[PDB]
Image (cartoon, rainbow, N blue to C red):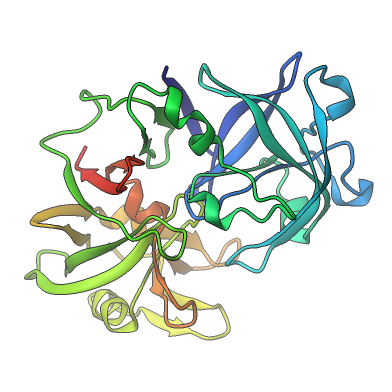
Length: 330
């Protein structure tokens, strides 16, 4: 089997991407944030505290003839941006782009933090990291991909995120028309539960490539590119007037600037992020200070190849017995 679904930016900045997901019988379609940095499929629901729902589409398990309470199971998750959610668990039929999994754990939110309530465009998350990170207790549950894997034509999924435009998540096949050149594959460590890999270096604009190992994660659920402070300083030094602002929370730059590209290495291959991809717009409406798309990871503990980086590539998440990642230009 295969599946293919379009993923759409939630706003004009590409802060996140939403993909329609069919849950239950008859189908209830929710728009979920596919997140290769986490491993829970959770949804706003008829159980979510009413004051914490503001415009999201909810899953109502009592209206699904295939829903079953997973007795005794609870979940609770916190994300790198400080947001969180928690609740109980049903199993139900879940379909993405024509690919169907029966008995998928659908984690129903009883509580969500304010940032979720305040974002009416995201109805939940669909985790695509390794199932070792799934938070369901006392019986850990498998991700949608883990459940689908054995049925897929090939045990892979691909992320093809658009810049200010829709893109595609495919399951079970590589679309050889979706990229240019060749796909360069690179080793993955699953020891932290992430799609963790080592970039071979970087360049700023037309500058020379610096060969240096940068361990980080391929994370579709993180908006920006978070790299070591040395790398980030080297980038922003090429933008007149850019500076790190503690009050704003990162590097800002004059909105009048033209940003240089940023290149990262994948083995001997190179992925070029155009400068425009690094502009996240005014820090507040009407400001002439703009927020940068490359930020320091120093306070995180891990480097994160988020959407800024991934949207410059066609990315293969190869879930074979020994997982690997592939990157191609497009």
